[PDB]
Image 1: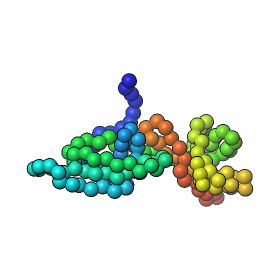
Image 2 (image 1 turned 180 degrees about the horizontal axis):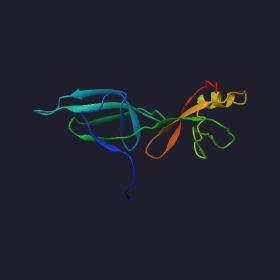
Image 3 (image 1 turned 135 degrees about the horizontal axis):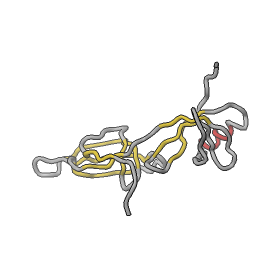
Length: 146
């Protein structure tokens, strides 16, 4: 069919390391990039080596330098954890409500997170936003006073 948001449109020559890019319909952080000539004049090919912002599973891409590759937005949001339980996450917010969604332990991060939590401490957990589907990444600590 068709949707739906994000992304942007950006020319393949533009982006650089640490930037974000949708490759094979998957959002990735740019890890390495190059520019070969093959051509002829006046030409170059951008070779983007990029890790997906979720699983990791390294992705590559070879496009004309001129070519426009789709770039995703990334919201990094540091919401406070509340309860697990379960099932799942949960968090709370700044603010707010919320969520009901999110599930990632992962982990490593899983383990950590639960072991946590179960000890004590109220935790700060950032979540990353890929077009629609999301997930946690950082697990932290508050600095409470008033």
